[PDB]
Length: 260
Length: 266
Image (cartoon, rainbow over all chains, first blue to last red; front, top):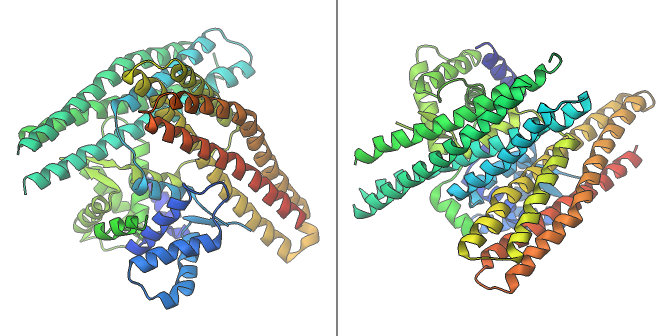
C-alpha cells in the first residue's frame, strides 16, 4: 500500500519508458530474426543497418535518409535498453522478452505442463529426502535450500508461464469465434478448448497433491532454518495460485460457452 | 523474411508505454507478484492507478475515467487479458520483470540448470536410440527437448544478457571513477574489475564443464532421427538447441576477452 507509491517514485525518478511505433517494433523484430538465426558471431553494426534497410524499404521510406535514420533507431534502442552496444550488438532481456512475444511460436499443449510437472516433482522429492536426514549448513544449503530456491522456484515460474500461454489461447479462440459470429466451427473451437482446460486441471490437480505433500514433508523437518521455511511458504502459495487459476479458467469458460 | 514486416505492418503492432503508463504497469506487476487468495479484479487495478495518478500529480476528479482508459489501453496493447478478471500476459510479464525482479547471478543456480538439462538430454537420447512408436517419439524425446531443455537454455541465455548489462554498467562506473582522478580511484576500479572478472570466469567455467556432454547427447538424438525420416521436427529442434548452446559458450568467451580487454585498457 505504501510500497507501490515508492515504486512509482522510483519509476518516475528513473524516467522509465518504452516507445515502439510499428516501424520501430518491426525493426526490433527483424533484428531478433538475426539474433536467433545468426551463425555464431554476434551482430555487427553493419548487420543492424542492413536490417533497418529492409524494414525501411518495406515501409516505403525515403532510401536517401537511411544511414541517418538507422543510426537514430539504433541509438534509441540502446537508450531505451532494448539493445546493448559493446566495444557489435546484443538484445537485452527487455528486447528479448518483447520480441519473443511476437516472433515466437509458443504453442500450448498439456504435454508441456506434464513435462514441467514431473521434473519439479523429482527435484522436490529429492530435496525432501535430503531434509529428512539432515546435516551441516553445507548439506542444508546445497541439497535443500538451493534445490528449492533455484530449481523448484524456477519451474513453478515456468508453469505459471505455461498457464499464461493457455490464457493467450483462450483469448485467441474468443477472437476467432468472434470472427465466425461476424456456427458449427464455433462449437468445435468451444469444445476442444474446454477439453484442454479440463485436461490441464486434472493433471495439475493430480500432481498438485503429490507436490504439496513433499513441501509438507520438508516443512516438518530447528532454529536458524527460517529462510528455508519462508521459501517453502510461498512455494506453496505459488502452487495453490496456479491450481486455483486452473479451476478459475475452466469455470469462466463455461460462462463463455453457454453464452453462445 | 521481410514479410514479418508485412505481418507487423498489416497488424499495427506497437508498444506505447510512457513513464506514467509503465509506472502503472510495474504497479500492476507488484500486485501480481505479491498476491494471497484470488486473481486481479478491476477494483485492485483501479486502486493501483490511483497511487500512480497521485504521485504524478494528476487530476483527481477524472481518476475513474482515466483508469478505465489506461486499463483498456493495456489490453489493446496486449500487456493484459481481461476475463469477464485481469491477468498479466507473457508480454506484460517479460517487460515487467526486466525492471522489477531481482538479478541473481549464482554459479550454483547455473550448475543445477545444467545438471537437470544433462539428465533430460541423456534420457531423450536413450529414448530415441531405442525409438518406439509415434506417441513414444512425441512424449519421450521431443517433449523433454522443447518443453524442458529449450526452456533452460532460454534462461541461461537470459542471465547471460542480465550479466551483459552488469558488465556495461560497471564499465560505465569505472569510466566515471577514473575521470575526476585516475590515481585515486584505481583501488575501487580494481575492485569492480576483478569482481566482474570473477563472475564471468566462474559462469563460463561451469558452462564449459557441461557443454561437451550436452553436445554429445544432442548429437545422439540427431543420429537416431536419420535412420528414420518422418522426424524432421525433432531434427530441427535438435539443430536449434545445438546452435543456441554454442552461441552461449561462444558469447561466454567473447565477454571474457572483452573484459580482459577493458582491464588492459586501465
